[PDB]
Image (cartoon, coloured by chain):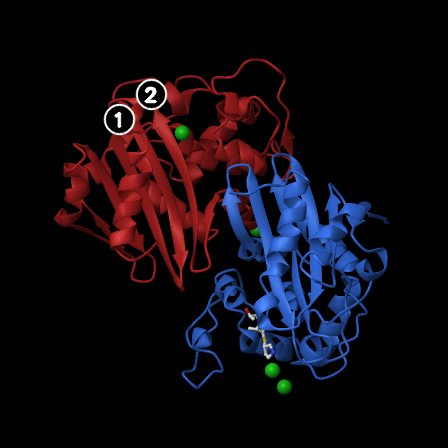
Chain colours: A red, B blue
Amino acid sequence: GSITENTSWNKEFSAEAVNGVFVLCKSSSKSCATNDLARASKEYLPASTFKIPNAIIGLETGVIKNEHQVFKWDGKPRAMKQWERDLTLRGAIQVSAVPVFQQIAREVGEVRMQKYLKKFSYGNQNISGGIDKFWLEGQLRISAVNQVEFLESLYLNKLSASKENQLIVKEALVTEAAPEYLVHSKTGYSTRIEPKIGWWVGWVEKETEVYFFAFNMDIDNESKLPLRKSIPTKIMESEGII
Amino acid sequence: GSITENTSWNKEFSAEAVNGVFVLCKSSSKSCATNDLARASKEYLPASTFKIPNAIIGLETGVIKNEHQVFKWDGKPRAMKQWERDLTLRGAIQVSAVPVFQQIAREVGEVRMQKYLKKFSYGNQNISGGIDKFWLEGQLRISAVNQVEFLESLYLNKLSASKENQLIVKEALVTEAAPEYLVHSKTGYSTRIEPKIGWWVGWVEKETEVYFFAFNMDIDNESKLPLRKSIPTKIMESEGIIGG
Ligand SMILES: [Cl-]
Ligand SMILES: [Cl-]
Ligand SMILES: [Cl-]
Ligand SMILES: [Cl-]
């Protein structure tokens, strides 16, 4: 593939006083563009974007039985009201139910989780910091470029997992369906350790083209969180994609 | 299965002067509700709702190579401008590209096509009338009850096809997505044999519940087509099944 720096996108960041990066890749020409090559290569806690490999590994290992599994709420208070209810696998991914995935990670265990992150070439592959929190406050780091490589492998079923399991997770990641296009995506927000990072990663299928994308930004306060989606959306709109 | 009449649903049909049926099943097809017991089991041409089994069959026979198949346009005139382009599976479904599906059916062939429709218990299972048009103007017929049974089997990966291929078709059928709400659906319009019939079939996931649905109605003219969606939408909303 190739990557090129495109300074024009900076307008959307400048207007918002945002420090951040977008990486957008057109599958047919294996060609990516970024507003910031340096930041595109910087490696940050994945936070809830880790739900993507974690769901695959959960299925691969038999910890998650299948896409019809329901994760029941035990009635104990959770950090968000939206998590205080039974959830499907898709629902637990889409509302970012950390408690559900901490449990999955515990059952997966260190030996197996390490093995998969190596197979997946996932970031620095460093799961230090406790088996249920390493993606949230441990030693794990991944870049925007690595996220797009990973998502392309998933799209093509080239990850070291069954196609069945890859498809289940693909199915779960759909976030917008229109007559002209389909969006798969996942957000993250790293807030336990400095610096505070918001992520939005995914891909768009339009006509017979596929566009993979990864976005991250420094988050000053919770009031900036929507720019996580709105800056990349604006860019993708300006490019005539969505 | 068991089918129970909900009297109150008729209001929605008589209020628009529509002859039609809606079938709705919560959790499973074991117990469904309808406005009309007789019509719920009446069988009609599937029209473009047949793209659902045909897509599964195309993948299972290897006629569609895999999820990333592109159906290439050779540049020769097609009947609609929306068809004059390369298409993905989801694209061909969205624009209702009947010529793409007809070429799939020809390559599948009558022997294989008959076998899968019988394994799937798909309507009267009659593919008489020409391999490229039996679902459009031939002898094939299916009811609203049988559509919900078929779609439930698809949802559960219980059709006689690989799980991989069932998942591929399901992704191409998503029409609405929200964190705890997901709709898979397909319209059809049968206009070659009287009476003309409109369909809307599908399923909805809401939180940890699932509902299977099938609607059909007599279509007098094109202007009544939207009802295919709004009458069943209103009834589903009456059951608390509400989208965004
Ligand atoms: Cl495999
Ligand atoms: Cl989040
Ligand atoms: Cl022919
Ligand atoms: Cl025809």
Given the current orientation, which residue lies at the most extreme top position? A76
Query: Residue A191 got which mark?
Result: 2
Asked which secondary structure carries label 1, the reply is: loop
Categorize mark 2 by other alpha carbons within 10 Å: few (<14), some (14-19), many (20+).
some
Amino acid carrying mark 2 in the image: Thr
Q: Nearer the viewer, residue A9 or A226?
A: A226
In this rendering, the answer to whether B101 lies above or below A210 is below
- Residue annotated with mark 1: A219
In this rendering, the answer to whether B98 lies above or below A1 is below
Q: Nearer the viewer, residue B38 or A48?
A: B38
Q: CA distance from mark 1 to mark 2?
A: 9 Å
Amino acid carrying mark 1 in the image: Ile
* Picture quarter with the C terminus of chain A: bottom left
- Residue A137, position as x, y percentages in the image: 36, 19
In this rendering, the answer to whether A76 lies above or below B178 is above
Q: Earlier in the sequence, mark 1 or mark 2?
A: 2
In this rendering, the answer to whether B195 lies above or below A35 is below
Asked if the residue under mark 2 is in contact with the one under mark 1, i.e. CB atoms within 8 Å, the reply is: yes
Q: Quadrant of residue B218?
A: bottom right
* Picture quarter with the N terminus of chain A: bottom left
